[PDB]
Amino acid sequence: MGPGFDFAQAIMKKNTVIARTEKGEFTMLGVYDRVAVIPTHASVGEIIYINDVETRVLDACALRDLTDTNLEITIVKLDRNQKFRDIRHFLPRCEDDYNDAVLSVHTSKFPNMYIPVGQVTNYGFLNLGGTPTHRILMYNFPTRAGQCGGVVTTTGKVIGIHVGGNGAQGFAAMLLHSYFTD
Ligand SMILES: COc1cc(C(=O)O)cc(OC)c1OC
Image (cartoon, rainbow, N blue to C red; front, side):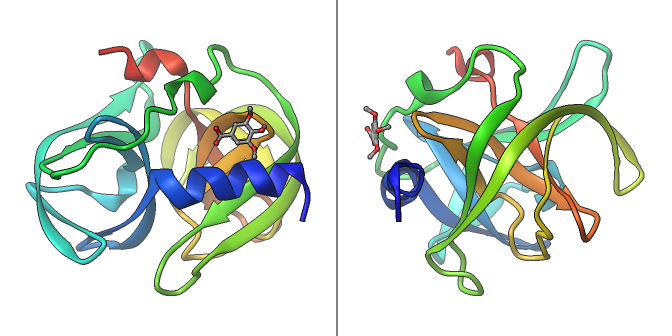
């Protein structure tokens, strides 16, 4: 409907797949080569379904900060026959607050879904499902089951992936450029 939705749609159309684990179907952001991200609570194993294709997992790393606190991001390398467009130049370098973000989701349950979530706070610490978590972004939208892994963007930046909510607020894990230096 506007330039925010334009950027979000460009990311969804080329850099997302539908990931299925034993814990559910998730929006999965492809970042470069065969490397993607997903919430850690997806519990990625040795095998994952990618757009309903059985796919070997070459590597999976559940990220933690240097205080050894959960970040809720798993980086997955997929045994896929095709690379993602490299979008690392759209990742922020530092923790920040943002204006006018979009949360985009693509699954069987929620195809081509885009939500204007407005202002995004650098919230920091969250007890996420009982797990102390750092680098959380917060937005005031009543996000639901089915939106986990959803991409959070502004115009020109891919800033986070949706990991939870409390009925009134939604919470995303930050994506930082430094996670994807190879
Ligand atoms: C349609 O929105 C954009 C898409 C892309 C892209 O390369 O996908 C790059 C942009 O910045 C130059 C955009 O504007 C912020």
